[PDB]
Image (cartoon, rainbow over all chains, first blue to last red; front, side):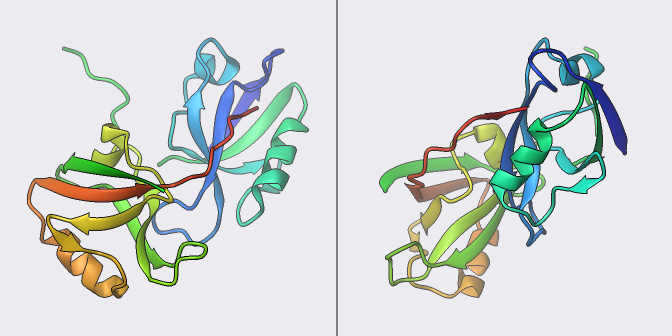
Length: 93
Length: 98
């Protein structure tokens, strides 16, 4: 699923970590946390654990942490992310 | 590495861990390492276990210097509460904000 975020001065509002998720041999980029108050938080679709596959068409799979982080910081005000959603977001009680 | 005793409470999806046999830098003996912590899983919810931590022992059974297949045999035959002895990974994971 594709997700477009409108960055503010604090950017996308994503804390990220490089890891090899269960079943994957390749290094991937994962959302550690969604910064409260930020663009990603307001959009609401992204959550901790989701994998960022592409940013503006560029692959974030099987590359070093430094290269992936560079691709993410060198984006424009509107960024297009290709996500892997890794079901119930909330529960009414 | 610092040692920690961890009593992990499983759920319906197990421990929520992906493990791998590898040798830590320097160590000659094979070790059982956490490759990944599954999001929303039991270990994830517990919060103490992290990728890179070494599982040394489970319910009194050693996991050091053994093949990867034997380790999984032990681990899947555990009860609801898993008594782990772990070696905490040393690296300081830097916060990357974008």
